[PDB]
Image: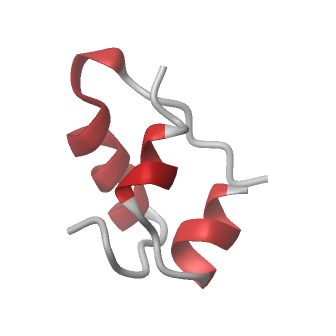
Amino acid sequence: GIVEQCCTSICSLYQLENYCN
Amino acid sequence: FVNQHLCGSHLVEALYLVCGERGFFYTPK
């Protein structure tokens, strides 16, 4: 999930926007 | 600010800034 993708690994705008409503 | 390791309040902040008026969901589990 987001923690794996953005905290443990390096985040990206593409991935962050998958969590916008 | 997006292209780095973002944890906890830092991650929530990034979601807030990117998503704007849409809002977002933060599901760490």
**Is A1 on the left or on the right of B22, as rendered?**
right
Q: A16 or B14, which is in the foreground?
A: A16
Please identify the quarter of the rendering in which residue A4 is found.
bottom right
**Is A7 on the left or on the right of A2, as rendered?**
left
Image position, residue B1 (x, y; %) = 20, 68
Image position, residue B25 (x, y; %) = 55, 32
Residue at position x 32%, y 74% from top?
B3
Report the coloring of the rendering: secondary structure
The outermost residue toward the front is A14
Image position, residue A16 (x, y; %) = 45, 49
Residue at position x 53%, y 69% from top?
A6
The outermost residue toward the right is B29
**Is A11 on the left or on the right of B10, as rendered?**
right
Residue at position x 62%, y 68% from top?
A5
**Is B5 on the left or on the right of A1, as rendered?**
left
Please identify the quarter of the rendering in which residue A20 is found.
top left
Residue at position x 54%, y 75% from top?
A7
Query: With respect to residue B11, does B15 lie above or below?
Result: above
Please identify the quarter of the rendering in which residue B21 is found.
top left
Query: With respect to residue B16, does B13 lie above or below?
Result: below
Count the numbered circles shown.
0
Image position, residue B8 (x, y; %) = 48, 65
